[PDB]
Image 1 (cartoon, rainbow, N blue to C red):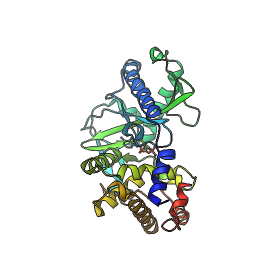
Image 2: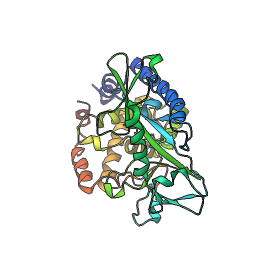
Image 3: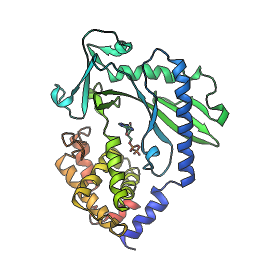
Image 4: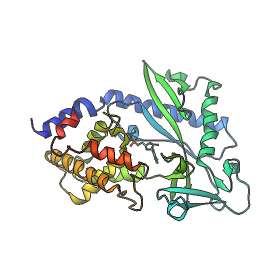
Length: 325
Ligand SMILES: Nc1ncnc2c1ncn2[C@@H]1O[C@H](COP(=O)(O)OP(=O)(O)O)[C@@H](O)[C@H]1O
């Protein structure tokens, strides 16, 4: 067996989600999203929100192995002249890709109630919606027309709803509060290290995945397929699960800037280059976002975690087949 064959087999038998399970899980999310729009509009009339919408690999057909999770973005409405955002590189935290949202001027904002010390706290905003999720046990049977049962998730996932749809099938939808100031999009997705957990996170995923799609659509290439394999590999072990979709996506994107030919027969070649690149970034302790180079996507990892990942992947260019096992 060529590495090529083993890669395609692994994708087919391990990475890929059955088209049925995949489409069905997506439709569950779509259905619930539409329901939560109507209901929460009446359940929280005072709260300045845009329409909520779905986001994540399940929505993008980049989810792997099993289809069980998706984000529901909750867009806060902010009066643009009552708030400004401060990029981390200009703060004392000095963390690019993470923002402060500072309260400004006069006026009143509904969201003043989540401001502490003159800043809109992502955690305080998150707590407003932990309340909403916990309150879901008071709601009527939403989606009961399409035989869905919505339940707050088992602790400690205080922002997650559990949706059971027939039968013994569950989809986990977490609320992801978001703010848009000018053209900067931020989400309350805590920095992995707690010190930075009250900084807002710059939303990079939509632009990352759009770039990935556009590149593959231009030439029917295999960038997405190679990515999905990596994502499923990194879901295989505890060690490798410290690697993220975003990190792997940007590994691919960087490699795409160097390699134009992503024909399906080049998959094994690209997979090794991807591993190679991944090892270099880990060696350097730096993986810059392809779309915003100022942002090091490895900056939520401790240097030891980074060294251990490097160790975990040390023999991968010469025993790659081992990752598929
Ligand atoms: N619009 C968005 N902006 C920023 N982050 C997002 C957005 N949608 C989802 N995310 C985040 O991206 C991560 C999931 O990325 P994803 O590609 O779904 O990886 P996986 O398939 O491994 O779950 C989650 O931590 C989630 O909070």
